[PDB]
Length: 156
Image 1 (cartoon, helix red, strand yellow):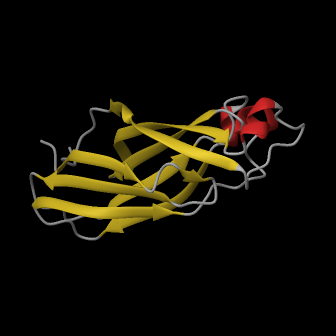
Image 2 (cartoon, rainbow, N blue to C red):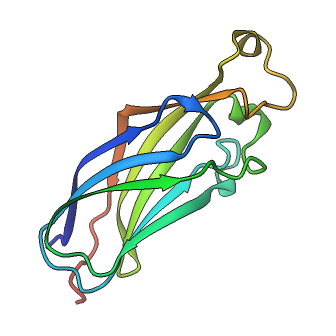
């Protein structure tokens, strides 16, 4: 009953300084023809300390999505640096790729990005205020936390 099934998903550009873009290569195969537009989203974890600081950055919508395996590149800029917390900025945050269909999201890709300063010295002594310009984003694409949700693609 699925209209879209993401098969190949990889993270590119990483690892690079935090001011790099969320570059994802999303290959999803549409099993059936979409009449509604597929809303792809990057909901990034704002704080592990308080996950309510989470923020969606960019959303790629394809109205309509024809049946077939499409491979598009998802690109968003860096998350709001004011939402990333002191003690968690120097750590591992998650970048979620949720796909909204009919107001219901059927998949959430949890990519763990490990953020550590590139300056070895700053790795030694993390300052009271993290330095996002020194911070390296190692998006561990080898660890894809795939949470899929069973929803109704058919409007029943």
